[PDB]
Length: 166
Image (tube, rainbow, N blue to C red; front, side):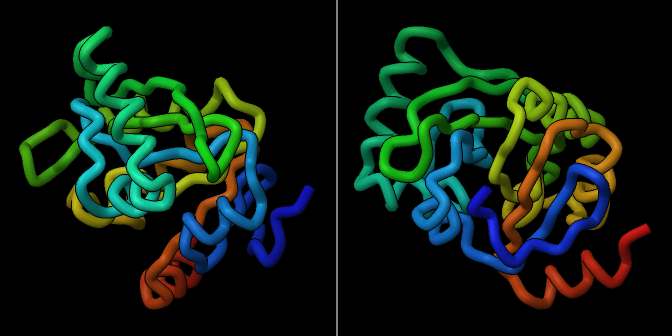
């Protein structure tokens, strides 16, 4: 495929220091993963960046989804359009540690990835969701069996994830 410049961590997990928006625009993957919240309000972090790249179409679609179906559950997901970034967007809700949500639900969140053969994704529950990114990467590797291409924006965090990997 057209994923380029990734470091192989395991048989099926790959990582790159890259902006996931820029990577999606270049590769046009079948699935890009959004780091969503249960209301699909794409205000900040990865979600805010992906939605802005779609010129707010992701938010309009999401609002219709919530009006029809109600909120997601922490650990859950839904598949919506990828707009100009991808065929599909898999919106996955990891726990937000700043809200007291149970970190054990991060494993449930990553299990959603197993329904898709290839994904471009961020580290779930990192950044503004408050979890330790080294832990998130460990759960990813121990849970996901399909092909995942992880994009980590912060170069200092990228170097720490690679250098500390077991």
